[PDB]
Image (spheres, rainbow, N blue to C red):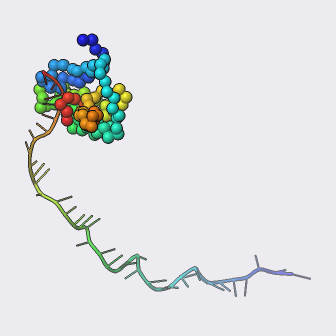
Amino acid sequence: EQFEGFVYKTNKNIGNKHDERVFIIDRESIEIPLSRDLRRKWRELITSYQEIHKKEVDRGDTGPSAVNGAVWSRQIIADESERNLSDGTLCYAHVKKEDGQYKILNLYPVMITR
RNA sequence: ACUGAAACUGUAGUAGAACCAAUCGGGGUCGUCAAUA
């Protein structure tokens, strides 16, 4: 198939990780209102990612001590610009179907998330 | 069409009486962290 879209390149965050993912915008798409609730949740979650390892990042560790062959995930080393959910920022959305509608629970920077 | 003279603003009087630098706090202890394939 031929597709187009964007690449959600994070980094080699895990030792078994081989691939980045790219968002096949060429096809089906669904738009959902961005509430202020999801905005604060993102900022709080991304603050958590960036603050938790601040000591490890500042002392110059290239990746988390507990996972070998791996480097900081994009959201951790990214700036506070990442912490603000600005126009065209890429995400994973945690979603379910209810009342016949796609409810969105959270926005997450990675597949298996904090 | 003759300058008055002479005279300590001084004497007595404790910036002091009362007031707590003090109240609370085991030098203690477990699972997280990373995200894909």
Q: Residue at x 34, y 38 (%)?
A: A35
Q: Residue at x 20, y 29 (%)?
A: A111
The image quadrant where one finds the N terminus of chain A is top left
Vertical placement of A38 versus A15: above or below? below
Q: Residue at x 22, y 21 (%)?
A: A21
Residue extending farthest top: A2
B31 to the left or right of A5: left
The foreground one among A82 and A68 is: A82
The foreground one among A92 and A76 is: A92
Vertical placement of A14 versus A54: above or below? above
Q: Is residue A35 visible?
A: yes
Q: Position of residue A10 (x, y in %)?
A: 23, 24
Q: Position of residue A107 (x, y in %)?
A: 27, 33
Q: Position of residue A48 (x, y in %)?
A: 24, 38
The image quadrant where one finds the C terminus of chain A is top left
Q: Is residue A80 visible?
A: no
Q: Residue at x 30, y 15 (%)?
A: A4
Vertical placement of A17 versus A99: above or below? above
